[PDB]
Image (cartoon, coloured by chain):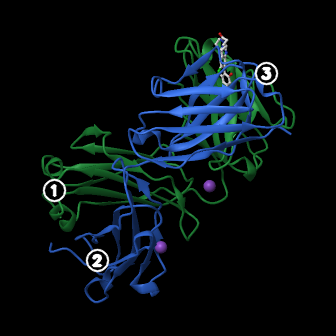
Chain colours: A blue, B green
Amino acid sequence: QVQLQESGGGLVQPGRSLRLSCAASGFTFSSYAMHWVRQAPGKGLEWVAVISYDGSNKYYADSVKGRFTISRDNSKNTLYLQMNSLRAEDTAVYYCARDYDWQYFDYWGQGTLVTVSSASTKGPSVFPLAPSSKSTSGGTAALGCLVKDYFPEPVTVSWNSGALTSGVHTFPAVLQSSGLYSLSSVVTVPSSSLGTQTYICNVNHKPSNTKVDKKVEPKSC
Amino acid sequence: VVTQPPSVSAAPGQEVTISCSGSSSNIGNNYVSWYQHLPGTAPKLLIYDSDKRPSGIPDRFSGSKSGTSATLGVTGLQTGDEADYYCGTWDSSLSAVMFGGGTKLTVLGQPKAAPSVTLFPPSSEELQANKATLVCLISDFYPGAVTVAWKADSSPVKAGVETTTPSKQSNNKYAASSYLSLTPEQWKSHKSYSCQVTHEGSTVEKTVAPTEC
Ligand SMILES: CCC(=O)N1CCN(c2ncnc3c(F)c(-c4c(O)cccc4F)c(Cl)cc23)CC1
Ligand code: NA
Ligand code: NA
Protein backbone atom coordinates (compact mmCIF):
# COMPACT_ATOMS: atom_id res chain seq x y z
CA GLN A 1 0.00 0.00 0.00
CA VAL A 2 0.82 3.68 -0.01
CA GLN A 3 3.15 4.73 2.82
CA LEU A 4 4.75 8.05 3.77
CA GLN A 5 7.59 8.51 6.27
CA GLU A 6 8.72 11.91 7.58
CA SER A 7 12.09 12.52 9.16
CA GLY A 8 14.51 15.28 10.11
CA GLY A 9 12.66 16.64 13.12
CA GLY A 10 14.33 17.43 16.41
CA LEU A 11 15.68 20.24 18.57
CA VAL A 12 16.76 23.41 16.74
CA GLN A 13 17.53 26.92 18.01
CA PRO A 14 15.47 29.98 17.04
CA GLY A 15 16.76 31.76 13.95
CA ARG A 16 18.55 28.65 12.68
CA SER A 17 17.35 26.35 9.90
CA LEU A 18 16.22 22.76 9.48
CA ARG A 19 15.32 20.47 6.58
CA LEU A 20 12.51 17.92 6.78
CA SER A 21 12.12 14.99 4.39
CA CYS A 22 9.15 12.78 3.52
CA ALA A 23 9.80 9.47 1.75
CA ALA A 24 7.00 7.95 -0.34
CA SER A 25 6.34 4.30 -1.15
CA GLY A 26 3.37 2.63 -2.72
CA PHE A 27 2.48 4.90 -5.65
CA THR A 28 3.87 6.86 -8.61
CA PHE A 29 5.28 9.79 -6.68
CA SER A 30 5.67 12.10 -9.71
CA SER A 31 1.89 12.02 -10.40
CA TYR A 32 0.77 13.67 -7.15
CA ALA A 33 0.92 17.01 -5.44
CA MET A 34 2.25 16.77 -1.84
CA HIS A 35 1.45 18.83 1.27
CA TRP A 36 3.02 19.72 4.59
CA VAL A 37 0.63 20.16 7.53
CA ARG A 38 1.61 20.81 11.14
CA GLN A 39 0.08 20.78 14.61
CA ALA A 40 1.49 22.98 17.36
CA PRO A 41 1.05 21.79 20.98
CA GLY A 42 -2.60 22.22 21.88
CA LYS A 43 -3.56 23.90 18.58
CA GLY A 44 -5.65 22.81 15.63
CA LEU A 45 -4.16 21.46 12.42
CA GLU A 46 -2.46 24.18 10.37
CA TRP A 47 -1.77 23.73 6.67
CA VAL A 48 1.81 24.69 5.76
CA ALA A 49 2.47 24.27 1.99
CA VAL A 50 1.76 22.25 -1.16
CA ILE A 51 3.87 21.51 -4.24
CA SER A 52 2.44 20.29 -7.53
CA TYR A 53 3.53 17.04 -9.17
CA ASP A 54 6.37 18.75 -11.09
CA GLY A 55 7.12 21.61 -8.69
CA SER A 56 5.98 24.35 -11.07
CA ASN A 57 3.23 25.40 -8.61
CA LYS A 58 3.83 25.90 -4.86
CA TYR A 59 1.60 27.56 -2.27
CA TYR A 60 2.37 28.54 1.33
CA ALA A 61 0.44 29.58 4.40
CA ASP A 62 1.02 33.25 5.23
CA SER A 63 2.49 32.24 8.61
CA VAL A 64 5.51 30.64 6.85
CA LYS A 65 5.69 32.40 3.45
CA GLY A 66 9.18 33.75 2.88
CA ARG A 67 10.77 31.52 5.55
CA PHE A 68 9.91 27.98 4.41
CA THR A 69 10.66 26.42 1.02
CA ILE A 70 8.84 23.31 -0.20
CA SER A 71 10.64 21.17 -2.76
CA ARG A 72 10.63 17.64 -4.14
CA ASP A 73 12.92 15.18 -5.89
CA ASN A 74 10.84 12.82 -8.04
CA SER A 75 13.89 10.65 -8.79
CA LYS A 76 14.23 9.80 -5.07
CA ASN A 77 10.49 9.77 -4.24
CA THR A 78 11.18 12.45 -1.61
CA LEU A 79 9.35 15.59 -0.48
CA TYR A 80 11.30 18.32 1.36
CA LEU A 81 10.51 21.27 3.60
CA GLN A 82 13.38 23.69 4.15
CA MET A 83 12.60 25.71 7.28
CA ASN A 84 14.57 28.93 7.79
CA SER A 85 14.46 31.67 10.42
CA LEU A 86 12.74 29.35 12.86
CA ARG A 87 10.57 30.84 15.61
CA ALA A 88 9.08 29.39 18.80
CA GLU A 89 5.64 29.25 17.16
CA ASP A 90 7.05 26.74 14.63
CA THR A 91 7.29 24.07 17.34
CA ALA A 92 4.93 21.38 16.07
CA VAL A 93 4.52 17.88 14.74
CA TYR A 94 4.99 18.17 10.96
CA TYR A 95 3.10 15.78 8.65
CA CYS A 96 3.40 15.18 4.95
CA ALA A 97 0.24 14.29 3.08
CA ARG A 98 -0.52 13.12 -0.44
CA ASP A 99 -2.92 15.27 -2.44
CA TYR A 100 -5.75 13.81 -4.47
CA ASP A 101 -6.76 15.79 -7.57
CA TRP A 102 -6.44 19.20 -5.87
CA GLN A 103 -9.48 18.12 -3.83
CA TYR A 104 -8.54 16.44 -0.52
CA PHE A 105 -5.71 14.78 1.41
CA ASP A 106 -5.80 11.01 1.16
CA TYR A 107 -2.61 9.57 2.72
CA TRP A 108 -0.49 10.88 5.60
CA GLY A 109 2.84 10.15 7.24
CA GLN A 110 3.39 9.45 10.92
CA GLY A 111 4.78 12.88 11.61
CA THR A 112 8.06 14.25 12.89
CA LEU A 113 8.37 16.57 15.88
CA VAL A 114 10.22 19.90 15.66
CA THR A 115 11.08 21.77 18.86
CA VAL A 116 12.42 25.31 18.56
CA SER A 117 14.28 26.33 21.71
CA SER A 118 17.59 28.01 22.56
CA ALA A 119 17.69 26.10 25.87
CA SER A 120 20.27 23.68 27.18
CA THR A 121 19.73 21.23 30.03
CA LYS A 122 18.46 23.17 33.04
CA GLY A 123 16.92 22.04 36.31
CA PRO A 124 13.66 23.55 37.53
CA SER A 125 12.85 26.26 39.98
CA VAL A 126 10.01 25.18 42.28
CA PHE A 127 7.60 27.72 43.76
CA PRO A 128 4.75 27.01 46.20
CA LEU A 129 1.10 27.41 45.30
CA ALA A 130 -0.05 28.12 48.83
CA PRO A 131 -3.60 27.33 49.99
CA SER A 132 -6.15 30.15 50.05
CA SER A 133 -6.25 32.32 53.16
CA LYS A 134 -10.03 31.71 53.08
CA SER A 135 -9.56 28.14 54.40
CA THR A 136 -11.59 27.30 57.52
CA SER A 137 -11.57 24.00 59.39
CA GLY A 138 -14.56 22.15 57.97
CA GLY A 139 -13.54 22.40 54.30
CA THR A 140 -10.85 21.35 51.83
CA ALA A 141 -7.91 23.30 50.44
CA ALA A 142 -6.04 23.06 47.15
CA LEU A 143 -2.29 23.53 47.37
CA GLY A 144 0.47 22.74 44.97
CA CYS A 145 3.74 23.68 43.43
CA LEU A 146 4.76 25.42 40.25
CA VAL A 147 7.71 23.67 38.55
CA LYS A 148 9.19 26.10 36.21
CA ASP A 149 11.77 26.85 33.61
CA TYR A 150 13.33 23.43 33.11
CA PHE A 151 14.64 21.59 30.06
CA PRO A 152 14.20 19.07 28.61
CA GLU A 153 11.25 16.93 29.67
CA PRO A 154 10.46 15.12 31.88
CA VAL A 155 9.92 16.08 35.49
CA THR A 156 8.27 13.73 37.98
CA VAL A 157 6.47 14.99 41.07
CA SER A 158 5.59 13.21 44.27
CA TRP A 159 4.22 14.51 47.54
CA ASN A 160 5.60 13.86 51.02
CA SER A 161 8.10 11.41 49.46
CA GLY A 162 5.31 9.19 48.11
CA ALA A 163 3.32 9.09 51.36
CA LEU A 164 0.61 11.38 49.94
CA THR A 165 -0.98 10.07 46.74
CA SER A 166 -4.75 10.49 47.12
CA GLY A 167 -6.08 13.71 45.63
CA VAL A 168 -2.91 14.52 43.67
CA HIS A 169 -2.98 15.66 40.06
CA THR A 170 0.18 16.54 38.16
CA PHE A 171 -0.53 18.44 34.95
CA PRO A 172 1.25 18.12 31.59
CA ALA A 173 4.00 20.61 30.90
CA VAL A 174 3.69 23.70 28.73
CA LEU A 175 6.56 24.94 26.60
CA GLN A 176 6.80 28.64 27.34
CA SER A 177 7.86 31.15 24.71
CA SER A 178 11.22 31.26 26.53
CA GLY A 179 12.04 27.79 25.21
CA LEU A 180 11.63 26.29 28.73
CA TYR A 181 8.96 24.00 30.19
CA SER A 182 6.72 24.57 33.21
CA LEU A 183 4.14 22.41 34.94
CA SER A 184 2.16 22.23 38.15
CA SER A 185 1.18 19.61 40.67
CA VAL A 186 -1.82 20.12 42.94
CA VAL A 187 -3.26 18.21 45.89
CA THR A 188 -6.56 18.65 47.73
CA VAL A 189 -6.13 18.22 51.48
CA PRO A 190 -8.32 18.85 54.56
CA SER A 191 -8.16 22.46 55.69
CA SER A 192 -8.09 21.04 59.24
CA SER A 193 -4.61 19.67 58.53
CA LEU A 194 -2.96 22.90 57.34
CA GLY A 195 -1.55 23.92 60.70
CA THR A 196 -0.24 20.48 61.64
CA GLN A 197 0.57 18.40 58.54
CA THR A 198 3.68 19.22 56.53
CA TYR A 199 3.23 19.12 52.74
CA ILE A 200 6.33 18.84 50.57
CA CYS A 201 6.42 18.38 46.83
CA ASN A 202 9.35 16.31 45.53
CA VAL A 203 10.43 17.29 42.03
CA ASN A 204 12.87 15.05 40.18
CA HIS A 205 14.52 16.24 36.95
CA LYS A 206 16.70 13.33 35.81
CA PRO A 207 18.21 15.08 32.72
CA SER A 208 19.91 17.64 35.02
CA ASN A 209 20.27 15.18 37.95
CA THR A 210 18.40 17.73 40.07
CA LYS A 211 15.89 16.92 42.79
CA VAL A 212 14.02 19.78 44.53
CA ASP A 213 11.87 19.35 47.65
CA LYS A 214 9.69 22.41 48.35
CA LYS A 215 7.67 22.86 51.53
CA VAL A 216 4.24 24.37 50.80
CA GLU A 217 2.70 26.19 53.74
CA PRO A 218 -0.05 28.76 54.43
CA LYS A 219 0.68 32.40 53.71
CA SER A 220 1.10 35.17 56.29
CA CYS A 221 -2.45 36.41 55.81
CA VAL B 1 -11.17 32.34 9.54
CA VAL B 2 -13.22 29.18 9.04
CA THR B 3 -14.74 28.61 12.49
CA GLN B 4 -16.33 25.59 14.18
CA PRO B 5 -17.79 25.09 17.65
CA PRO B 6 -15.08 24.04 20.13
CA SER B 7 -17.02 21.03 21.47
CA VAL B 8 -20.03 18.84 20.71
CA SER B 9 -21.27 15.73 22.50
CA ALA B 10 -24.00 13.08 22.64
CA ALA B 11 -24.49 9.59 24.03
CA PRO B 12 -23.56 6.34 22.23
CA GLY B 13 -26.13 5.56 19.56
CA GLN B 14 -27.23 9.21 19.29
CA GLU B 15 -26.25 11.70 16.58
CA VAL B 16 -24.44 15.03 16.31
CA THR B 17 -23.72 17.63 13.68
CA ILE B 18 -20.62 19.78 13.35
CA SER B 19 -20.70 22.86 11.13
CA CYS B 20 -17.97 25.13 9.96
CA SER B 21 -18.68 28.65 8.83
CA GLY B 22 -16.61 30.41 6.23
CA SER B 23 -17.03 33.04 3.53
CA SER B 24 -17.57 33.09 -0.23
CA SER B 25 -13.84 32.94 -1.00
CA ASN B 26 -13.49 29.60 0.85
CA ILE B 27 -16.50 27.44 1.87
CA GLY B 28 -18.82 29.34 -0.46
CA ASN B 29 -17.07 28.49 -3.73
CA ASN B 30 -14.72 25.58 -2.96
CA TYR B 31 -14.53 21.87 -2.17
CA VAL B 32 -15.09 21.06 1.50
CA SER B 33 -13.60 17.92 3.06
CA TRP B 34 -13.81 16.59 6.63
CA TYR B 35 -11.11 14.83 8.68
CA GLN B 36 -11.10 12.84 11.91
CA HIS B 37 -8.01 13.35 14.04
CA LEU B 38 -6.83 11.79 17.26
CA PRO B 39 -3.60 13.70 18.04
CA GLY B 40 -0.49 11.56 17.87
CA THR B 41 -2.17 9.70 14.99
CA ALA B 42 -2.66 10.75 11.37
CA PRO B 43 -5.85 12.54 10.26
CA LYS B 44 -8.40 10.34 8.48
CA LEU B 45 -10.54 11.45 5.54
CA LEU B 46 -14.28 11.18 6.25
CA ILE B 47 -16.08 13.24 3.60
CA TYR B 48 -14.86 14.86 0.38
CA ASP B 49 -16.54 17.14 -2.15
CA SER B 50 -18.88 18.28 0.67
CA ASP B 51 -20.92 15.03 0.68
CA LYS B 52 -19.03 12.03 -0.77
CA ARG B 53 -17.75 9.20 1.40
CA PRO B 54 -14.47 7.43 0.60
CA SER B 55 -14.43 3.66 0.52
CA GLY B 56 -14.44 2.24 4.04
CA ILE B 57 -16.27 5.16 5.69
CA PRO B 58 -19.71 3.99 6.94
CA ASP B 59 -22.94 5.66 5.87
CA ARG B 60 -23.46 7.09 9.38
CA PHE B 61 -21.03 9.85 8.34
CA SER B 62 -22.60 12.37 5.98
CA GLY B 63 -21.92 15.89 4.80
CA SER B 64 -23.77 18.84 3.37
CA LYS B 65 -22.99 22.37 2.26
CA SER B 66 -25.30 25.39 2.27
CA GLY B 67 -24.03 28.81 1.28
CA THR B 68 -20.93 29.70 3.28
CA SER B 69 -21.37 26.93 5.87
CA ALA B 70 -20.70 23.20 5.73
CA THR B 71 -21.97 20.48 8.04
CA LEU B 72 -20.79 17.01 9.03
CA GLY B 73 -23.41 14.66 10.47
CA VAL B 74 -22.56 11.60 12.55
CA THR B 75 -25.26 9.14 13.55
CA GLY B 76 -25.03 5.94 15.57
CA LEU B 77 -22.26 7.45 17.67
CA GLN B 78 -19.76 5.08 19.21
CA THR B 79 -16.76 5.70 21.45
CA GLY B 80 -14.40 5.08 18.55
CA ASP B 81 -15.79 8.32 17.11
CA GLU B 82 -14.42 10.45 19.95
CA ALA B 83 -11.79 12.62 18.24
CA ASP B 84 -11.10 16.08 16.86
CA TYR B 85 -12.96 16.90 13.64
CA TYR B 86 -11.74 19.43 11.10
CA CYS B 87 -13.22 20.71 7.91
CA GLY B 88 -10.73 21.71 5.25
CA THR B 89 -11.15 23.88 2.18
CA TRP B 90 -9.39 26.13 -0.34
CA ASP B 91 -9.60 29.91 -0.10
CA SER B 92 -9.52 31.37 -3.62
CA SER B 93 -8.48 34.84 -2.42
CA LEU B 94 -5.52 33.72 -0.32
CA SER B 95 -4.53 30.75 -2.51
CA ALA B 96 -4.21 28.61 0.61
CA VAL B 97 -5.80 25.63 2.32
CA MET B 98 -7.64 26.55 5.50
CA PHE B 99 -8.63 24.15 8.26
CA GLY B 100 -11.54 24.99 10.48
CA GLY B 101 -10.61 25.49 14.11
CA GLY B 102 -11.49 21.92 15.07
CA THR B 103 -14.31 20.45 17.15
CA LYS B 104 -13.80 17.92 19.91
CA LEU B 105 -16.49 15.24 19.65
CA THR B 106 -17.16 13.65 23.04
CA VAL B 107 -19.15 10.44 23.18
CA LEU B 108 -20.76 10.79 26.61
CA GLY B 109 -19.82 8.02 29.03
CA GLN B 110 -20.18 9.73 32.39
CA PRO B 111 -22.20 12.58 33.98
CA LYS B 112 -21.54 16.11 32.85
CA ALA B 113 -19.67 18.13 35.48
CA ALA B 114 -18.94 21.86 35.53
CA PRO B 115 -15.34 22.80 36.37
CA SER B 116 -13.91 23.84 39.67
CA VAL B 117 -11.50 26.73 39.10
CA THR B 118 -8.66 27.54 41.49
CA LEU B 119 -6.68 30.68 40.71
CA PHE B 120 -3.30 31.13 42.42
CA PRO B 121 -1.65 34.58 42.45
CA PRO B 122 2.15 34.78 42.08
CA SER B 123 3.91 33.43 45.16
CA SER B 124 5.99 35.79 47.28
CA GLU B 125 9.05 33.71 46.36
CA GLU B 126 8.45 33.98 42.62
CA LEU B 127 7.88 37.72 42.92
CA GLN B 128 11.19 37.99 44.78
CA ALA B 129 12.76 36.13 41.84
CA ASN B 130 11.44 39.01 39.66
CA LYS B 131 8.75 36.88 37.96
CA ALA B 132 4.97 36.68 38.24
CA THR B 133 2.93 33.69 37.08
CA LEU B 134 -0.80 33.35 37.62
CA VAL B 135 -1.78 29.68 37.76
CA CYS B 136 -5.36 28.78 36.87
CA LEU B 137 -6.11 25.12 37.71
CA ILE B 138 -9.34 23.70 36.31
CA SER B 139 -10.56 20.40 37.69
CA ASP B 140 -13.35 17.83 37.86
CA PHE B 141 -15.08 18.63 34.61
CA TYR B 142 -16.65 16.59 31.83
CA PRO B 143 -16.77 16.65 28.78
CA GLY B 144 -13.04 17.33 28.60
CA ALA B 145 -13.11 20.56 26.63
CA VAL B 146 -12.81 24.12 27.94
CA THR B 147 -11.98 27.57 26.65
CA VAL B 148 -9.80 29.73 28.90
CA ALA B 149 -9.63 33.51 28.73
CA TRP B 150 -7.67 35.92 30.89
CA LYS B 151 -8.64 39.45 31.90
CA ALA B 152 -6.57 42.27 33.37
CA ASP B 153 -9.08 44.35 35.26
CA SER B 154 -11.70 43.79 32.56
CA SER B 155 -9.68 43.85 29.34
CA PRO B 156 -8.72 40.71 27.36
CA VAL B 157 -5.14 39.49 27.77
CA LYS B 158 -3.64 37.35 25.03
CA ALA B 159 0.14 37.76 25.44
CA GLY B 160 1.86 35.41 27.85
CA VAL B 161 -0.91 32.78 28.09
CA GLU B 162 -0.22 29.03 27.94
CA THR B 163 -2.95 26.42 28.44
CA THR B 164 -2.69 22.65 28.64
CA THR B 165 -4.99 20.24 26.86
CA PRO B 166 -7.42 18.59 29.33
CA SER B 167 -6.38 15.14 30.53
CA LYS B 168 -7.91 12.69 32.98
CA GLN B 169 -7.65 12.80 36.76
CA SER B 170 -7.67 9.77 38.97
CA ASN B 171 -11.41 9.99 39.43
CA ASN B 172 -11.90 9.83 35.61
CA LYS B 173 -12.98 13.48 35.22
CA TYR B 174 -10.79 15.99 33.36
CA ALA B 175 -8.44 18.71 34.57
CA ALA B 176 -6.57 21.43 32.71
CA SER B 177 -4.22 24.27 33.60
CA SER B 178 -3.57 27.75 32.29
CA TYR B 179 -0.71 30.16 32.95
CA LEU B 180 -0.45 33.91 32.58
CA SER B 181 3.21 34.97 32.73
CA LEU B 182 3.54 38.56 33.89
CA THR B 183 6.18 41.02 34.86
CA PRO B 184 5.98 41.93 38.58
CA GLU B 185 5.36 45.48 37.36
CA GLN B 186 2.58 44.31 35.03
CA TRP B 187 1.15 42.39 38.01
CA LYS B 188 1.08 45.30 40.47
CA SER B 189 -0.23 47.84 37.92
CA HIS B 190 -3.75 46.38 37.73
CA LYS B 191 -6.51 46.22 40.29
CA SER B 192 -7.33 42.59 39.52
CA TYR B 193 -6.76 39.66 37.19
CA SER B 194 -9.26 36.99 36.18
CA CYS B 195 -9.20 33.47 34.78
CA GLN B 196 -12.44 32.77 32.84
CA VAL B 197 -13.26 29.20 32.02
CA THR B 198 -16.01 28.36 29.53
CA HIS B 199 -17.43 24.82 29.62
CA GLU B 200 -20.57 23.66 27.77
CA GLY B 201 -21.97 27.16 27.42
CA SER B 202 -21.42 28.22 31.02
CA THR B 203 -18.54 30.29 32.37
CA VAL B 204 -16.75 30.17 35.73
CA GLU B 205 -14.55 33.18 36.48
CA LYS B 206 -12.12 33.46 39.40
CA THR B 207 -10.45 36.74 40.34
CA VAL B 208 -7.30 37.65 42.27
CA ALA B 209 -5.83 41.06 43.15
CA PRO B 210 -2.28 42.15 44.03
CA THR B 211 -3.62 43.98 47.10
CA GLU B 212 -5.57 41.05 48.58
CA CYS B 213 -4.44 37.70 49.88
C1 LIG C 1 -1.37 24.35 -9.60
C2 LIG C 1 -2.58 24.36 -10.50
C3 LIG C 1 -3.46 25.54 -10.13
O1 LIG C 1 -3.33 26.60 -10.64
N1 LIG C 1 -4.49 25.36 -9.16
C4 LIG C 1 -5.65 26.35 -8.53
C5 LIG C 1 -5.76 26.43 -7.02
N2 LIG C 1 -5.65 25.35 -6.49
C6 LIG C 1 -6.93 24.78 -6.02
N3 LIG C 1 -8.06 25.03 -6.66
C7 LIG C 1 -9.23 24.50 -6.25
N4 LIG C 1 -9.31 23.71 -5.19
C8 LIG C 1 -8.18 23.40 -4.48
C9 LIG C 1 -8.25 22.55 -3.31
F1 LIG C 1 -9.45 22.02 -2.94
C10 LIG C 1 -7.10 22.25 -2.58
C11 LIG C 1 -7.14 21.31 -1.38
C12 LIG C 1 -6.46 20.10 -1.50
O2 LIG C 1 -5.77 19.81 -2.68
C13 LIG C 1 -6.45 19.19 -0.44
C14 LIG C 1 -7.13 19.49 0.72
C15 LIG C 1 -7.84 20.68 0.85
C16 LIG C 1 -7.84 21.58 -0.23
F2 LIG C 1 -8.50 22.76 -0.16
C17 LIG C 1 -5.90 22.80 -3.00
CL1 LIG C 1 -4.35 22.56 -2.21
C18 LIG C 1 -5.83 23.61 -4.12
C19 LIG C 1 -6.98 23.93 -4.86
C20 LIG C 1 -4.81 24.51 -6.82
C21 LIG C 1 -4.95 24.08 -8.26
NA1 NA D 1 2.66 13.07 40.14
NA1 NA E 1 -13.67 12.03 26.95
Q: Are marks 1 and 2 in contact (CB under 8 Å)?
A: no
Q: Which residue is mark 3?
A: A31
Q: Amino acid at mark 2?
A: Val
Q: Which residue is mark 2?
A: A216
In the figure, residue B47 lies in which quadrant? top right
Q: In the rendering, at what x and y percent does residue B54 appear?
A: 83, 30
Q: Amino acid at mark 1?
A: Pro
Q: In the rendering, at what x and y percent does residue A156 appear?
A: 46, 72
Q: Are marks 3 and 2 in contact (CB under 8 Å)?
A: no
Q: Which residue is mark 1?
A: B210
Could you say which is closer to the camera, residue B74 or residue A92? Answer: A92
Cα–Cα span, label 3 and label 2:
62 Å
Report whether B110 appears left or right of A116: right
Which residue is pictured at 74% across the width and 32% down the height?
A76
Q: Nearer the viewer, mark 3 or mark 2?
A: 3
Q: Check disc 2 and report its element: helix, strand or loop.
A: loop
Asked if badge 1 and badge 2 are on a common chain, one would say no
Mark 1 chain: B
Relative vertical location of residue B84 with respect to residue B24 in this rendering, above or below? below
Residue B99 shows in the view: no
